[PDB]
Length: 237
Length: 300
Ligand SMILES: CC(=O)Nc1ccc([N+](=O)[O-])cc1
Image 1 (cartoon, chains in turn blue, orange):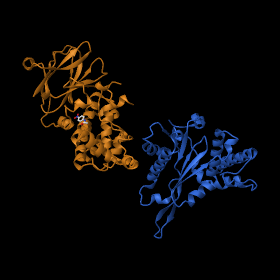
Image 2: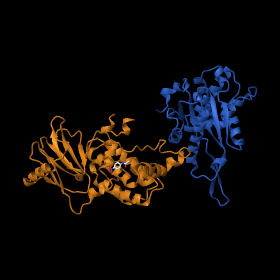
Image 3: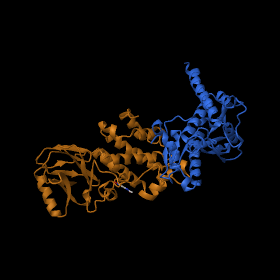
Image 4: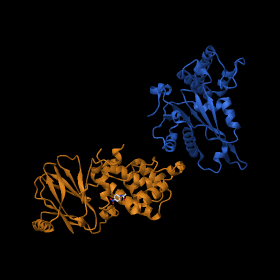
């Protein structure tokens, strides 16, 4: 059934699973027309498909041409997501296909279930966790490849950089969700924290800065402060 | 006009015949039902006074043979049987009629209710749903599972209704996933009407049979089937115009006949609100929508 705080370590067992987040698939800017009406302009989006055990991220870029001439785009976006996730699974060798796909939004359950009818043994599950994957587009290198795309494209990343050499996947996922929660609550501050010290760089093949273990503890403490703050600045506490 | 005689009534029982019912006391001198209209299927059904559990009964068509009821004290129920000796049967019935030991099928002449509930029901096609090899009549009771339900555990004494499943490969063409799920016209018209039923009369017959088993026996799988067959039509953007008009009439008379106090269990809120207010056919069921809104506005 649904994934929650109680069965959290299941994410890091040896059954292949993927999170799918669709919140950045259909993206628009809202603007005024010359007549003073309102209109939308689509911008490029992405499907965020993540193996939480390995850090492997399958970033399917959604180019704005896929919406041309289509109606009810927010509904179509869920079905397009499911189409692309199904195509990804079919592209993988059998031994790499997931045994479960966890969707971050319940509205993805029926579209993905219907697209995966060929795979009756792959479980499609919701979650009660409020995961911050919408903030993936606050990661500069991810945002950059999405905005530069001129055609549909799949780009593969490891969202944990080399962390698994030093920490477990449980700890890596916890760091990732802390970073992303911070970026979602106050992007400017979070990004300031991450880059304030210019002697710590992002390797060309990485997404995040090359912190030592001790600097990560400081960084992580700064992100918690940020999140509790904003939680005060917000509710006044 | 045909007759279903009873050998006797050894146990106190409420007896139904179609939408009518009457109480018989233990060892009351009751010997059956006369003046049954020819041309329609019928159902004769039973609820014992001591065990309101298990309503049960028999679908039959008097044109297909001479049928009677006899209590079996070993199996503890009223059983339908066929009498092959036509002279023995005429003589039994004539004596019971002479002694006025029979209730009269009590049809008002203005009343088309039973016709309207059984217009497409066929008794030869109930050899698909309940193939109890030898029987010309068909036993149904409250607990009977569907054949489909054996897979989500006895299928020759079950309801072999047509398997409808909206998230199935049968319902969804590869490459048309979103289209076929949001508009079920290809599943309705190509898969079900052209491939399985053969015509809409057959589609309406199983839909009518499903409703009647839900109403008379509280058969839960029958209620599921009735709602699925409604929802498949309402969720299709493309439906023959004559089918929509006929469906409105079918459902109107079903909703009219439903006991007011059973609406809580026999009507699925989700299906009816979707069908009447969200679906492609939301504007196509005027008679049904009006009776539903005046009789069960709570459900909506
Ligand atoms: C496949 C198919 O025609 N089934 C079916 C047709 C009619 C009835 N019926 O009761 O009239 C029951 C089942």
